[PDB]
Image 1 (cartoon, rainbow, N blue to C red):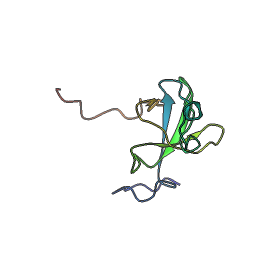
Image 2: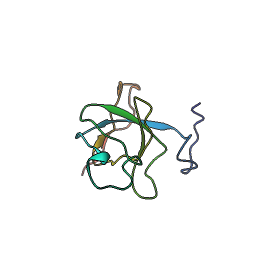
Image 3: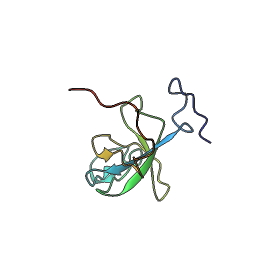
Image 4: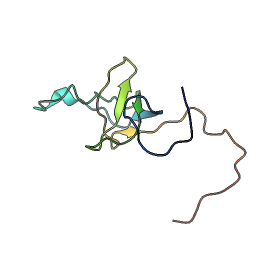
Length: 96
Protein backbone atom coordinates (compact mmCIF):
# COMPACT_ATOMS: atom_id res chain seq x y z
CA UNK A 1 0.00 0.00 0.00
CA UNK A 2 0.91 3.66 0.27
CA UNK A 3 1.59 4.64 -3.32
CA UNK A 4 2.22 8.34 -2.82
CA UNK A 5 2.25 11.13 -5.38
CA UNK A 6 -1.28 12.15 -4.50
CA UNK A 7 -3.41 14.48 -6.59
CA UNK A 8 -7.09 14.30 -5.73
CA UNK A 9 -9.53 12.19 -3.75
CA UNK A 10 -9.81 9.14 -5.97
CA UNK A 11 -11.75 6.69 -3.84
CA UNK A 12 -13.03 6.98 -0.29
CA UNK A 13 -12.39 3.31 0.37
CA UNK A 14 -8.82 2.41 -0.50
CA UNK A 15 -6.85 5.65 -0.43
CA UNK A 16 -4.51 6.54 2.41
CA UNK A 17 -6.09 6.37 5.84
CA UNK A 18 -5.93 8.79 8.75
CA UNK A 19 -5.88 7.95 12.44
CA UNK A 20 -8.19 10.11 14.52
CA UNK A 21 -9.03 10.01 18.21
CA UNK A 22 -12.64 10.60 19.17
CA UNK A 23 -12.68 13.99 20.86
CA UNK A 24 -16.03 13.31 22.48
CA UNK A 25 -17.89 10.06 23.04
CA UNK A 26 -20.49 9.87 20.30
CA UNK A 27 -23.28 7.44 19.51
CA UNK A 28 -25.31 7.48 16.28
CA UNK A 29 -27.60 4.76 17.58
CA UNK A 30 -28.58 7.02 20.45
CA UNK A 31 -30.88 9.25 18.44
CA UNK A 32 -33.79 8.81 16.02
CA UNK A 33 -31.17 8.73 13.29
CA UNK A 34 -32.62 6.39 10.70
CA UNK A 35 -29.07 5.78 9.54
CA UNK A 36 -27.07 5.31 12.74
CA UNK A 37 -25.17 2.37 11.31
CA UNK A 38 -23.87 4.75 8.67
CA UNK A 39 -21.92 6.65 11.30
CA UNK A 40 -19.65 5.25 13.99
CA UNK A 41 -19.90 5.38 17.79
CA UNK A 42 -16.94 7.58 18.64
CA UNK A 43 -15.44 7.17 22.09
CA UNK A 44 -13.52 10.09 23.56
CA UNK A 45 -9.96 8.81 23.63
CA UNK A 46 -10.58 5.88 21.31
CA UNK A 47 -9.08 5.93 17.84
CA UNK A 48 -10.29 5.13 14.34
CA UNK A 49 -9.02 4.90 10.78
CA UNK A 50 -10.71 7.19 8.28
CA UNK A 51 -9.83 6.30 4.71
CA UNK A 52 -9.52 9.06 2.14
CA UNK A 53 -10.80 12.43 3.29
CA UNK A 54 -13.97 14.41 3.89
CA UNK A 55 -17.03 12.78 2.37
CA UNK A 56 -19.59 14.33 0.05
CA UNK A 57 -21.69 14.91 3.15
CA UNK A 58 -18.73 16.07 5.21
CA UNK A 59 -17.93 13.00 7.27
CA UNK A 60 -14.99 10.66 7.75
CA UNK A 61 -15.20 6.98 6.89
CA UNK A 62 -13.50 6.11 10.15
CA UNK A 63 -12.90 2.42 10.74
CA UNK A 64 -13.41 1.53 14.38
CA UNK A 65 -10.65 -0.58 15.88
CA UNK A 66 -13.28 -3.29 15.93
CA UNK A 67 -13.52 -3.00 12.17
CA UNK A 68 -16.68 -0.92 12.26
CA UNK A 69 -16.89 1.12 9.08
CA UNK A 70 -19.06 4.22 9.00
CA UNK A 71 -19.16 8.00 8.85
CA UNK A 72 -17.37 10.12 11.43
CA UNK A 73 -17.65 13.84 12.23
CA UNK A 74 -14.35 15.69 12.15
CA UNK A 75 -15.84 17.75 14.96
CA UNK A 76 -15.70 14.69 17.17
CA UNK A 77 -12.40 13.27 15.99
CA UNK A 78 -8.85 14.45 16.59
CA UNK A 79 -6.28 13.43 14.00
CA UNK A 80 -3.95 11.73 16.45
CA UNK A 81 -0.31 11.10 15.62
CA UNK A 82 1.95 8.18 16.46
CA UNK A 83 5.21 10.10 16.53
CA UNK A 84 5.19 13.51 14.88
CA UNK A 85 8.94 13.92 15.15
CA UNK A 86 10.03 12.33 11.89
CA UNK A 87 12.15 14.74 9.88
CA UNK A 88 14.70 17.29 11.02
CA UNK A 89 12.30 19.92 9.73
CA UNK A 90 13.43 22.41 7.11
CA UNK A 91 10.62 24.95 7.04
CA UNK A 92 8.73 26.57 9.89
CA UNK A 93 5.12 27.67 10.46
CA UNK A 94 3.63 30.99 9.44
CA UNK A 95 2.06 33.83 11.40
CA UNK A 96 -1.68 33.64 11.93
